[PDB]
Image (cartoon, rainbow, N blue to C red; front, side, top):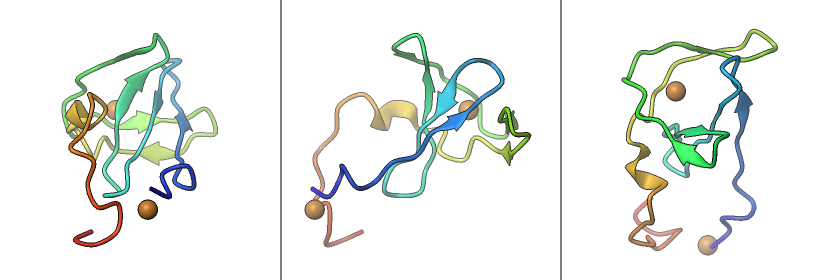
Length: 74
Ligand SMILES: [Cu+2]
Ligand SMILES: [Cu+]
C-alpha cells in the first residue's frame, strides 16, 4: 500500500486544493468534498504563489480505483 506515505496538497487560491497520485499526476479535488473537472493547462496558483499546472486532468483516479500493485509496474 504505502499509500499513507504518499501525500500532496497545494492550497489553491480558489479555496480548493489539488492532490497528486503515485503517477505524479495531479487531482482537482474541491474542498467541497467533491471533484471538479479542470481542463488541462488551467494554471493553478497557490496562496504562496506557487505556479502549478493541472497536469493530471484525469480526476477519474479519485473516483475509486483498480487498486494497482502499488509497487510493481509503476
Ligand atoms: Cu505498497
Ligand atoms: Cu486543477
